[PDB]
Image: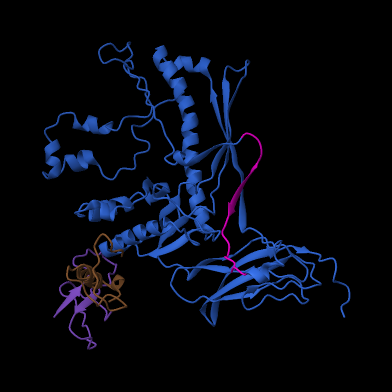
Chain colours: A blue, B purple, C brown
C-alpha cells in the first residue's frame, strides 16, 4: 500500500494563501485574520487524495473512521440522438435515391407522328452510405474483491452499477463526438453551401447581418418551388421550416441572446426560425452555425450488444459493449454552413450526372453548378481527360464521345480563380462509362 | 435634407471593424459626395472613405 | 434605392411601398396604375406584393 504522502500533490499553487498572504498585509486577506483554524482549513480545503491512517486524538490506539461514502453518479447523453434514423439488421450499404424534374416539350402534332415511342430517361441521382464505426467498450468488474472496499451493500451495489453507467455514458459521449465529426468532415469536403459572414463577435452589425442571412437562407430553403442549390447534388429540393435545424456553437448563442434578443422589441423577428440546437463543436476554422434539413443526418445503428464473460479462476466479469454504427450524411438533404473569415471564391463545382454512361459516338450534355461565395462570373472550362481520338467536350458541357472511344472518361468542370500568375482551380467532375455502339462502326463511306 | 448613417447604434469589438453606410435623403441625385469621419478615442481608430 | 444597400434605402422603400399601396386603393381610383390608362381601384385584400 502507501506510506507517507505530502498534503499536496497536484497543487501547482498560484500563491501562498497562508503565511505569505493571509499572515502578511492588512488588505483583502485581513478578513481571514480572525479565523482560528484557517491554516488547517486551507491546508486541506480542497480535500485529499490519500486517506492516510489517522489515530484518534484521545485514544492513540483507536483509529478514526470514514463516516460517509458518497458515490456520485452521472448520466451523459448525446444532444444529437434525436437525429438518429433507425436500426439496420443486415447489410452494409444504404442506398439513397432521389428523382428530379425534366424539361417541357413543345406540343407539335404533325412532327410527333413519328415520335410516339420516342423516349427519355428520368433525371435520377443516387448516393451511398455505409457502416462506419465498429468499436467497443471493455470494462472489467472484480466484484468479489470490490466487496472489501465497502461496508454497506447499498454503496457496494451503487458502485458496481456506477461502473456499468460509465459504459453507455462513454457510448453517448462518443456517439455525439462522431456526429460532430460528420459535420466537420462534410465541411472539410467543401460540401456545405457556404454563406460568408463576418465574425459576429467583432460587431453587433456583423451579428445583425448574420441574423439576416440566417433568416433569409431559411426562407429560401423552404420556398414551395424548391431550389436547385443548397445541397451537394445540385438537385431541386425543398425543406420545411420545422424540418430545419440550426446548430449553434455555444458562445454564439450568448452573443445573439445578449446583444440582439434582449433588445429586440418584437423578438420573433430576429428569431433563427429553425430548431436551434446548441453544441460545443465546429472543430474547424470559421465554421459556425450549420443549418440543415432534419434528414441530413443518416445515422443508423448496426449493433448494440453487451457481451459478458467471467473468469472463474480470477473473480471478475468482463463487459464488452459493442457499438457498430453507420455514420454519414445526405447530400440530397439541404445543408448550409455559415462561415466567418475569408473563404474561396468557389467552394465546389457539381457536374450534373456523376455517372453518364454513353455509347461510342454519342454525347451527353453536362451542366456545371458553381457554388460561388461571391456573386459573379466563374465561367467553367470543360475537359474530358480520357482518351485521345475524336472525343472532345465542347465549350459547354456537351461531351461528344467518339466512335473509337473505349476508356472511361472524366469530365472536368474547372473554375479558374485568382491572379493569372497565381491561378487556382476549383474542379468538379463526373465519369463516363463507355459502351460499344455495335453497328455503324469499322469503316465509313 | 438629411444623412442617415445606417448603423444607428453599434458596438465594436476592439481590433475589429464596422462598415457604415450613409443614406442621403435628398432632392435630385446631384452626386452628393459623403465625407466620413470619426470622433474621440486614440490614433488606433480611423475610418475610410467607404 | 436598391435598399439591401442600406437601412435608409430600406426605409425609403417601405415608405414608397406603403404610400404606393395606398394610392392604388384610394376610393376615387386612378389611371396611373394601369397600362390601359383607365380609372381603376384596387383593394388591400387584392394587392399582392
Q: Is residue A392 left or right of residue C40?
A: right
Q: Quadrant of residue C31?
A: bottom left
Residue A361 visible? The answer is yes
Look at 55% across and 39% down and name the residue there.
Answer: A300
Q: Is residue A393 left or right of residue A23?
A: right
Q: Which residues are magenta?
A: A89-108
The C terminus of chain A - image quarter: bottom right
Instruction: From the top left corner, tell me how far across and down residue A328 is, in percent.
Output: 55, 47
Q: Nearer the viewer, residue A142 or A223?
A: A223
Instruction: From the top left corner, tell me how far across and down residue A262 is, in percent.
Output: 21, 52
Residue A66: in magenta span: no
Q: Nearer the viewer, residue C49 or A382?
A: C49
Q: Main secondary structure of the magenta part?
A: loop
Q: Quadrant of residue A37?
A: top left
Look at 34% across and 62% down and name the residue there.
Answer: A199
Report the residue that reaches farthest toward the bottom. Answer: B30
Amino acid at each position: 500500500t502507501f506510506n507517507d504522502v505530502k498534503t499536496s500533490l497536484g497543487i501547482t499553487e498560484s500563491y501562498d494563501i497562508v503565511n505569505a498572504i493571509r499572515n502578511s498585509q492588512g488588505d483583502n486577506f485581513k478578513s481571514y485574520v480572525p479565523l482560528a483554524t484557517a491554516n488547517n482549513v486551507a491546508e486541506v480545503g480542497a480535500g485529499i487524495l490519500i486517506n492516510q491512517t489517522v489515530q484518534n486524538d484521545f485514544i492513540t490506539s483507536l483509529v478514526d473512521r470514514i463516516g460517509l461514502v458518497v458515490i456520485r453518479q452521472v448520466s451523459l447523453n448525446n444532444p444529437l440522438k434525436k437525429f438518429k434514423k433507425g436500426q439496420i439488421p443486415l447489410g452494409r450499404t444504404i442506398e439513397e435515391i432521389y428523382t428530379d424534374i425534366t424539361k417541357e416539350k413543345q406540343y407539335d402534332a404533325e412532327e410527333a407522328e413519328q415520335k410516339v415511342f420516342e423516349r427519355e430517361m428520368p433525371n435520377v441521382k443516387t448516393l451511398f452510405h455505409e457502416r462506419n464505426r465498429q468499436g467497443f467498450y471493455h470494462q472489467t468488474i472484480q466484484d468479489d474483491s470490490l466487496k472489501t472496499a465497502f461496508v454497506s451493500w447499498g454503496n457496494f451495489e451503487s458502485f458496481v452499477s456506477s461502473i456499468i453507467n460509465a459504459i453507455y455514458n462513454s457510448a453517448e459521449v462518443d456517439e455525439y463526438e462522431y456526429m460532430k465529426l460528420l459535420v466537420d468532415n462534410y465541411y472539410s469536403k467543401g460540401l456545405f453551401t457556404t454563406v460568408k459572414i463576418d465574425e459576429p463577435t467583432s460587431s453587433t452589425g456583423a451579428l445583425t447581418e448574420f441574423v439576416k442571412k440566417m433568416r433569409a437562407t431559411a426562407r429560401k430553403l423552404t420556398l414551395p418551388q424548391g431550389s436547385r442549390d443548397w445541397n451537394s447534388m445540385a438537385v431541386r429540393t425543398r425543406s420545411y421550416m420545422e424540418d430545419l435545424h440550426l446548430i449553434i456553437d455555444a458562445d454564439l448563442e450568448a452573443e445573439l441572446d445578449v446583444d440582439v434578443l434582449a433588445k429586440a422589441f418584437n423578438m420573433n423577428r430576429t428569431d433563427f426560425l429553425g430548431n436551434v440546437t446548441v453544441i460545443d463543436g465546429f472543430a474547424s476554422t470559421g465554421l459556425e452555425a450549420v443549418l440543415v434539413d432534419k434528414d441530413w443526418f443518416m445515422v443508423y445503428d448496426n449493433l448494440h450488444k453487451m457481451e459478458t464473460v467471467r473468469n472463474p479462476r480470477g473473480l471478475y466479469w468482463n463487459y464488452y459493449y459493442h457499438v457498430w454504427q453507420t455514420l454519414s450524411v445526405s447530400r440530397f438533404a439541404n445543408a448550409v454552413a455559415f462561415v466567418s473569415g475569408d473563404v474561396p471564391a468557389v467552394t465546389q463545382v457539381i457536374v450534373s450526372p456523376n455517372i453518364a454512361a454513353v455509347k461510342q459516338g454519342g454525347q451527353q450534355q453536362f451542366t456545371a453548378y458553381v457554388r460561388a461565395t461571391n456573386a459573379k462570373d466563374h465561367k467553367v472550362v470543360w475537359s474530358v481527360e480520357g482518351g485521345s481520338t475524336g472525343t472532345a467536350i465542347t465549350g459547354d458541357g456537351l461531351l461528344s464521345v467518339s466512335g473509337n472511344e473505349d476508356n472511361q472518361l472524366t469530365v472536368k468542370a474547372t473554375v479558374d480563380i485568382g491572379t493569372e500568375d497565381k491561378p487556382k482551380l476549383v474542379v468538379g467532375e463526373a465519369v463516363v462509362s463507355i459502351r460499344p455502339n455495335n453497328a455503324s462502326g469499322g469503316a465509313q463511306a
